[PDB]
Length: 4
Length: 4
Length: 138
Length: 138
Ligand SMILES: [Zn+2]
Ligand SMILES: [Zn+2]
Image (cartoon, rainbow over all chains, first blue to last red; front, side):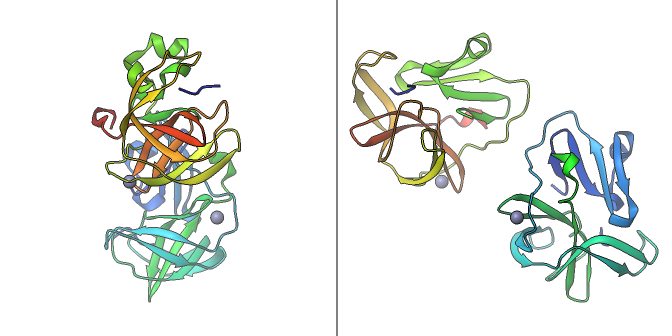
């Protein structure tokens, strides 16, 4: 799960 | 001018 | 429905304004059939920053959205009614289209946001009060 | 941007939640990567009441909206990251598409309103966390  |  | 809510403003036909509109009056113009009142909530609408002369509006009497082509805003002599005497109404954009009693207040929209609101009609025309110059709303 | 505002709710990726989100927590689910917090203003969004599997989302890295076709929500094993250990993520819809660091939070929309929010991606896929079953938001 992403959020970079 | 409308408003009926 | 029947109003534009932008920021902390509510824009309505002047002739349809409520007591609460007048209590919270910000600005009004009989020659445009427009009234703006203060709201406590932030609105969802955006005023179109454009010169579009095609868009879509909601027709109250048909409960349908219709596509429409309309004239550039103009000064138009509007005949007497129970709402105004015969007068010049400015900022008025005309389209061919259906209208009936109770259609005033329908919002006209394009890809850039809100363009205007149904104000007048008759003889096969619908007249929309342009709001796009009221840059202080947004 | 990066959140869905519906009624007095704000929906965000759990892994991107703020201190103020946690202070005003309503609901959170690590297995969905979702968190909902209370707001003081009313939001403008609507949750799609539908089963659409095509729509448009905003891509942060490209600053563009893209049309997308995506799978029905499913349980998907998602590999470890600095945000979660390897785990099953539920309610996840996959599309072929571009993604880069910082794309999580982009909102996926159809004709019926908000469908989901970018949560995961990699190997040429973008995974969106479906929100359409959260009927209590709207
Ligand atoms: Zn326009
Ligand atoms: Zn839909």
